[PDB]
Image (cartoon, rainbow over all chains, first blue to last red; front, side, top):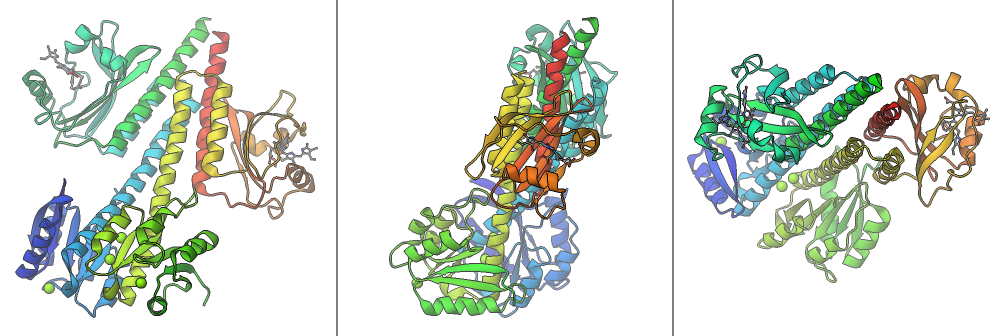
Length: 307
Length: 307
Ligand SMILES: CCC1=C(C)/C(=C\C2=NC(=C\c3[nH]c(/C=C4\NC(=O)[C@H](C)[C@H]4CC)c(C)c3CCC(=O)O)/C(CCC(=O)O)=C2C)NC1=O
Ligand SMILES: CCC1=C(C)/C(=C\C2=NC(=C\c3[nH]c(/C=C4\NC(=O)[C@H](C)[C@H]4CC)c(C)c3CCC(=O)O)/C(CCC(=O)O)=C2C)NC1=O
Ligand SMILES: [Mg+2]
Ligand SMILES: [Mg+2]
Ligand SMILES: [Mg+2]
Ligand SMILES: [Mg+2]
């Protein structure tokens, strides 16, 4: 049973209660239910809570359902709205679906099972469209970096292009590349930042975990994906440390050269926690692998000079 | 009215079937040709022989239960999803729920159907199958690209990398033949690796040494410009190329230049040998991306040469 936020927008307190009772009868999910009796507040709750689905009464005191959809501006998001219409007004349902709704229900004909089916579909379909959009953007990033590696030997340009595009794609506060010194200490080679996190470049913090251990887990590929340093169960030493650079969410991907650990591709969220998705993690492993190709390429260019 | 959609209705009631067809008339947006079957066996035959855009399936047929039917449906490999809409009697929603886990896209309740609801349900099933297809292909091409990147990162033998590109590309594309063309210093050319299917007679061991097009007619190939022929007889080609292509039984031709540094190293070639083929953007962009990776692969092998 996963969690779902469902927003009900209907001016009849009883219908809201009816729908609320119906959604609880769903074994597949646990629903957090938000309510509004007016369109304007519906819009406000929508904008503040990003609910997974919206049950929308076509006839509200302030807005008709069509006006509500038109007052919605949504990356490139899709609206998980189910229009609720009265029997006989199906023509509204059709023009609502052409305006962005995912499905509709007939008020007096609604059953719990039908409600589940509607919510499932609106959510699944928006998820498909969201995933497809993410696949397209993720492909642009990978191809753009592939392009760079084919067009140049220089690291400063490839790493830079990498750091920027991932920050753009992920909408992260910070992305940078951390490089290990021979004495297993670290420095930030490149960076790209949003002004919500206290900088790290030029202000170097000395950790003792990489000098002492050398990162054998990172050599053999270990990645860390911390959604929120306060709920992941880290030690008090680590939590307090990250709080001083305002890192709230942490994603770290090792960069490998030869059979050795060259450095780290690092993503930060500094304002709020962030649950890193499988697609995003997979993107970074891939880029890191391309960086390995770049580094290797640059070293073969160094070796070829000396000859 | 020109028919835009083919719908297969599988239901043992001739009256309900005609009823649904009339409902479909109320959709001004589309024109429906309806195939009808009263039995599972005939439904399956009609499905397999005529490839309808969507299916309305009665959960209870005289010979097969709706679930048993879905299990006998095999979908083409370029559209692996079943655009089936289950029709169940009320109270039997639970059977329909198990159908959507078995591949149906949606369901309807027998006595509750309205013309608009039928339209939207058919609309939805076709759009969702299309979304699911697009997402499915994005995942496959990313795997292909990610697999070649890995190989390059591992510094594996290039001919093995070339092999992998050639094989995996033909599978993803359902193409009759894919191969890699390599230029000799004297601007001729030979076929290094290949992947060929039923409809196509192979070309690899009988390579004709072509003229110096790379100097003037590969002006575009040096500058990275690709050729994408849907049908060699309508592309406006000269007799020499047309006759040449016909001697290899090429009907559709997609060729992508392979670059090493900024020089024309060779060509990635895709062929359809049976029928003409309109090459789609996803397919072309995949090929360009692979072409660039082979370019990066070629660079890795040359840099290891002096060293
Ligand atoms: C933001 C700027 C910055 C950081 C984060 C940095 C050090 C830093 N310490 C790290 C990990 C670490 N550092 C420590 C711990 C310590 N290190 C010590 O010097 C202590 C003795 C000790 C506890 C006080 C630990 C426990 C980790 C995490 C190790 C793990 O991954 O399990 C990491 C990698 C994981 C991460 O990014 O969270 C870095 C980059 N230096 C910097 O300039
Ligand atoms: C097994 C397959 C095979 C081929 C396809 C090959 C030759 C071959 N000739 C090509 C182009 C070409 N080849 C020719 C012309 C000629 N070529 C000649 O051998 C002529 C004597 C001459 C006719 C006058 C032309 C005009 C092109 C296309 C140039 C362009 O469109 O840029 C191409 C690349 C473009 C394409 O195929 O569309 C190849 C690979 N040798 C092979 O073993
Ligand atoms: Mg109302
Ligand atoms: Mg429905
Ligand atoms: Mg649906
Ligand atoms: Mg029947």
